[PDB]
Amino acid sequence: VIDAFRLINANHEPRQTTSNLGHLNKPSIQALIHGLNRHYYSITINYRKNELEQKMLLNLHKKSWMEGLTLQDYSEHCKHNESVVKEMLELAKNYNKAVEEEDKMTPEQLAIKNVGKQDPKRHLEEHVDVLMTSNIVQCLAAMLDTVVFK
Amino acid sequence: DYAKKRGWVLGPNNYYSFASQQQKPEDTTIPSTELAKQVIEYARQLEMIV
């Protein structure tokens, strides 16, 4: 949240118009209340950047290369998998207990069925995505290493 | 003559080995390229728009 200003004198229109470049921002209610376009006027802000700035701003979030080919402590892998599956067991039970409804529930009542109560479907979707991504990545790393280093 | 026709060692008299071992295949090399392709295809089908 940022903006650039300048002062309007006591003279009419403060500035002249030869494009739509001024009128693209829809000034906020608070700024108007506190004096915008009455005592001061805004100016468009441009964040233009050169080539080397662009190249380093892209290079901040980049980890070392070794991190790419590091496996996980396999024991921790298995513990994580068994924990999530032991959660999916109960989530599947609740999914069953919840699909049986949705017929004996008013079309409006459903929109409130899920407020303060776990929903099995969404959690199952999240856990399935997590499990499947993690396992695929670990497997691929293991195979890729198995080949690269002798 | 019939033993000659077939691939029999013709050992001691009336003693010919049939090589029932079938080489007893035990060597394993961890075929990886196939496994890597398989996994990348899982990921492909997982992330494409269907």
Image (spheres, coloured by chain):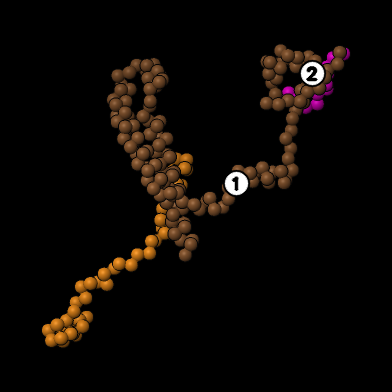
The residue closer to the viewer here, A70 or A107, is: A70
Could you tell me which secondary element the residue under label 2 belongs to?
A: strand
The CA span between labels 2 and 1 is: 43 Å
Q: Residue, x 21% and y 76% (percent of image)?
A: B19
Q: Chain of mark 2?
A: A
Q: Is residue A35 visible?
A: yes
Give the image location of residue B15, x and y in percent. Answer: 14, 82
Rate crowding at label 2 as few (under 14), some (14 to 19) or many (20 or more) other CA atoms within 10 Å: some
Q: Is residue B40 visible?
A: no
Q: Which residues are magenta?
A: A11-24
Q: Which chain is orange?
A: B
| Magenta span contains residue A117 | no
Which residue appears farthest toward the right when viewing the image? A11
* Residue A41 placement: quadrant: top right
Q: Indicate which label's residue lies in the foreground, 2 or 1.
A: 1
Q: Is residue B28 above or below residue A99?
A: below
**Amino acid type, residue under disc 1 in the picture:** Lys
Q: Is residue A116 above or below residue B25?
A: above
| Magenta span contains residue A13 | yes
Q: Which residue is mark 1?
A: A62
Q: Are marks 2 and 1 in contact (CB under 8 Å)?
A: no
Could you tell me which secondary element the residue under label 1 belongs to?
A: loop
Q: Which residue is mark 2?
A: A40
* Residue A108 placement: quadrant: top left
Q: Does label 2 or label 1 sit earlier along the sequence? A: 2
Residue B1 shows which numbered tag? none
Q: Residue, x 31% and y 28% (percent of image)?
A: A94
Which residue appears farthest toward the left when viewing the image? B14
**Amino acid type, residue under disc 2 in the picture:** Tyr
Q: Image quadrant for the C terminus of chain B?
A: top left
Q: Which chain is brown?
A: A
